[PDB]
Amino acid sequence: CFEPSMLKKKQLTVLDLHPGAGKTRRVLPEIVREAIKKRLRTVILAPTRVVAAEMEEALRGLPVRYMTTAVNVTHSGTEIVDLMCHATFTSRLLQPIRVPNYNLNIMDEAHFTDPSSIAARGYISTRVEMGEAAAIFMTATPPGTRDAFPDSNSPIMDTEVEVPERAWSSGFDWVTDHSGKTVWFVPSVRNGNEIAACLTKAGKRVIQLSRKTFETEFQKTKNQEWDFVITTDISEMGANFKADRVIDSRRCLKPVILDGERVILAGPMPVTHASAAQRRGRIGRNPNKPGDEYMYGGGCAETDEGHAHWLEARMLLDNIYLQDGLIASLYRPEADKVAAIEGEFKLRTEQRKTFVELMKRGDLPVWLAYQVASAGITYTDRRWCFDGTTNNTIMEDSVPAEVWTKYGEKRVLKPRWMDARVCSDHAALKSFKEFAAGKR
Ligand SMILES: Nc1ncnc2c1ncn2[C@@H]1O[C@H](COP(=O)(O)OP(=O)(O)NP(=O)(O)O)[C@@H](O)[C@H]1O
Ligand SMILES: [Mn+2]
Image 1 (cartoon, rainbow, N blue to C red):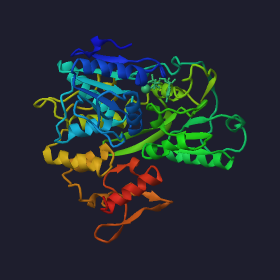
Image 2: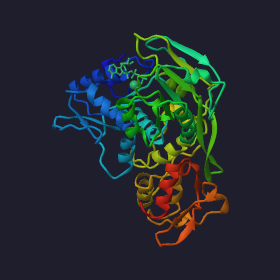
Image 3: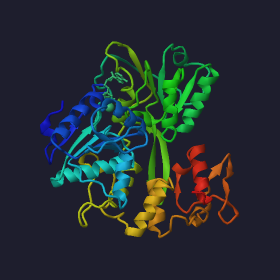
């Protein structure tokens, strides 16, 4: 549980109650009330805008400044408690914007493996180690967890079973014979597309979720009748469903940097124990409803090792001012996950601005944004999208993708640096084509 002693400077506490135990809805407001009593300048970090909106409900009445348009409230001026998304925190730290030296740093769903969340944990844990601050990381699955089957509010039926990853017609009757509501974790948007299409043809009502569609589509899980939610790993971060079954492929894609020169999406390959526990954790949450089902289609492995997100986190952290020339280290339990030289990605003022703009407005992956900024290219200079090797040709429906450049010339998309995440699904490619065309 929480104790006021956890609010003392130099304290970092991992509140690791099992999934559903009440960390976000019960323990968080307790902490916040105590922080306010103690006049502690406090930041609450929500993984997503959806979760931020839910927190406003659990925190209602309390004087919290919601630094998100996801929440519709008139703020007073009392507020010494701020709430923002993980990514917003890290983004503000990278920009010349002033962010308070928060006395207390509360990160909910602190297992989130997005680069900006990893970087935020590194920054926060370094501030605490410096003796400057306290921190509470709230997650059922702290870094390095080896338990894929933690406690739950009610008993879960765990079953190892072959899970389809492609359209099927026979041999998987248990999937469609089910009468309730299923959350199905897939390794990618495209894989989810195929499974969704198959289910829809079988007469099921399907909602699909991924990182860029999560806000709009998640509301459909409330506003619309559904049989299946097909989701990527984004739903591991405190997403609440009224479901009675989870189907878990136990698979994910792993961005991997090859030879420091390109990023591939490796796999699909096993999820971590933490990811598996969070996926399973979507059900068994109602103590009055035993027998929720968890079907899983493979084992776990430590696939965060060598995963690009921890290298990308270093790129972010190398560019956040801490004190003089010091550079914050990653949070200790996840600091092995990357082989990097601390400070090696530090950029000077102008290149850092370019780096930030390429990630924000550019919506480029961190790794790719870094290659461009560190090469001395300015944000609006898109010549690099076209002057790569033939091997870097991006394909769309089996034919090289083409755009009209801002000069009006039709050119094949051949980026100088290839990051597979810019074309891993239709939406990603659409966005990158707009970028290469100078439209953003
Ligand atoms: N909208 C809701 N209204 C009432 N009860 C709810 C609601 N949503 C969830 N609950 C219940 O409240 C409990 C506390 O939820 P929550 O505080 O999110 O747990 P948690 O420990 O943070 N879960 P996790 O992030 O998966 O480790 C859940 O286990 C549900 O049983
Ligand atoms: Mn939670």
